[PDB]
Amino acid sequence: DLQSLPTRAYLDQTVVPILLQGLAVLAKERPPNPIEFLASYLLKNKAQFE
Amino acid sequence: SLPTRAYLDQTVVPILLQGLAVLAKERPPNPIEFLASYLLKNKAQFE
Amino acid sequence: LPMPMRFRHLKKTSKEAVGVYRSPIHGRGLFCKRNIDAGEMVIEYAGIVIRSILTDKREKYYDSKGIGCYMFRIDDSEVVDATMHGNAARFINHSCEPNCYSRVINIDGQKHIVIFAMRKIYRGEELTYDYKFPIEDKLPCNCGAKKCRKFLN
Amino acid sequence: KQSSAVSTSGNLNGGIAAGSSGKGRGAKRKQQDGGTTGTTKKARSDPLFSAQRLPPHGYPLEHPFNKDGYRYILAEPDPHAPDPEKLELDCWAGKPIPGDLYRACLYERVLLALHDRAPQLKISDDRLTVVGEKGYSMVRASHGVRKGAWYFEITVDEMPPDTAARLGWSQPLGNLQAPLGYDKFSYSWRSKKGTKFHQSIGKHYSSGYGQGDVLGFYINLPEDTETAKSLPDTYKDKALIKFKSYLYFEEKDFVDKAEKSLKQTPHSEIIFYKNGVNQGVAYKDIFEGVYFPAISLYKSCTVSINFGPCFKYPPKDLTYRPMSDMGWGAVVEHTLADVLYHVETEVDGRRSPPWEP
Ligand SMILES: Nc1ncnc2c1ncn2[C@@H]1O[C@H](CSCC[C@H](N)C(=O)O)[C@@H](O)[C@H]1O
Ligand SMILES: Nc1ncnc2c1ncn2[C@@H]1O[C@H](CSCC[C@H](N)C(=O)O)[C@@H](O)[C@H]1O
Ligand SMILES: [Zn+2]
Ligand SMILES: [Zn+2]
Image 1 (cartoon, helix red, strand yellow):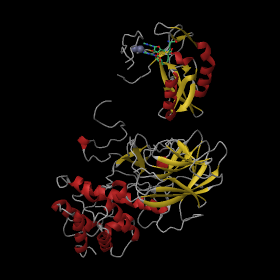
Image 2 (cartoon, protein in one colour):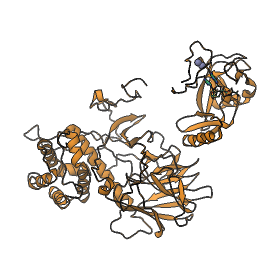
Image 3 (tube, helix red, strand yellow):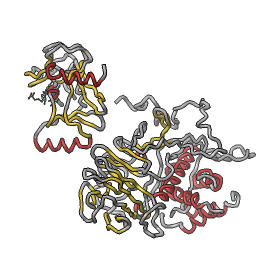
Image 4 (tube, protein in one colour):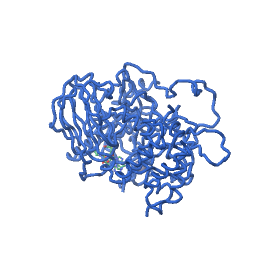
């Protein structure tokens, strides 16, 4: 079902909006550990869109 | 501080792109904790 | 000549240039009373200038009153509705071979729909233009032209 | 009326499905020097040339405002989404992501977007007031809310008796010629007596309005979870056009919704204030879809929208956000949208973190 979709479709049909918002907040806050700040942000907020 | 696009390109976009590759290739059941783990462990090569 | 000057001349001569009589096309229609040259201003379809969004509310209104809609689209934003207030241009029949043609002009910022003459029109001729009505699913035409589409739509 | 072939205007043709990935073949690659557009990295000058400002209200002369569900935005060249680094030993490692475009907005701050006004709508950037001449019309701001709670104001500078502005919110699908509440996707207030107008229906569940009212507007929509309960993906459309003398971008907007079932966004509401004093709740039932603050003009109405950092009677909430904050939030979001679309078309693969944010 979800794995049979093309690249554009599956990668769209799964995850786009969090990148949309998290990359935004990452550019807004300008943290010293950008990759690590994103990692902390996501490991805190894993669940509530899924 | 760089502009939005330039800052994100210099800070997160390449490791993001390699994660893009791996997610498009292996197609895990739970990509959520997949990128969790990936962005945690592969950060050292782009810090 | 200036479109304003030409328009003033047209509004001055309109009352004596054209008439309305019994028409072999259908009922009553616009006939030429003085030889009209090609491209010159025949008549304004004068009426109530309204915005497009208000058309339907008017139309349904007339649909509630059993009064026929006399509306011509100026453009995507304006319409001259002549149902309640208009001029003699409400009696111009259509022909598949028109000696006239509708054009929108801008005078002092306001748009006027003027029927001009596709050719040199002579006295007595009935005035007809291309309504360009979109194809519906059917109004038979009796314009008499050999090229007649048999239907406006 | 011809066939599934070349576009309706020979001025510029986008690559059809049979000509897939056909980039807009507009201006040729051979450019002139110009000088005015030869800005470098060392200079400090905003490339988005704002027009000359005039105290009397004016009209954007060569902007084809939205129509037929077709959104129209400013364009800038942006020859390279910046990814330049040193020459790596591996010549097949990085991707330039040459979108050759961006949604750069001709605005110093989050203001009333000129792209979404009617041709009968005049603006004065001395106060960014909006005015009209015949009947009603509608204008909207640059930003648009999708979640959270936020707040702005409208300042009224002129209200004769034959002058009645209306102020509120409206989702896309809102016909900017209608008086901000003629459809079910818009909820406003009539500035004669405080009267909530929606679906063209007037309701007196409201306070009274004053001629010199500096009115505050608070509005809280739930997170995109309770808004969609599903994927809020934002796959964007981008088309390049070269109008008479300037480059612009076209995108596909939403279609007229036949929604007749009531499914209010959970815990969403709208509150109205007169100079900060609570005029009360306006609409608790709020349909899904993004909303934006909007202003409707009657004959010669003078009103203006205003953000938070220069406020007069602001709420002291730590969660609500001014107009400017959500504005740059949405701007950065659409920047990332361009990033992701150029990624999709340019480099294989995509990947986003643990979904929740
Ligand atoms: N060429 C044509 N073929 C068929 N019907 C026509 C026609 N031209 C005009 N008509 C009919 O005539 C009507 C004109 S409305 C005018 C009514 C009537 N002729 C009168 O003078 O009082 C239209 O509703 C249309 O049905
Ligand atoms: N070719 C045609 N077929 C059917 N109706 C026509 C027609 N050309 C004009 N009409 C009529 O023209 C009207 C719109 S304009 C009215 C002009 C008409 N000569 C009149 O005397 O009133 C319609 O109601 C229609 O009935
Ligand atoms: Zn005919
Ligand atoms: Zn005919």
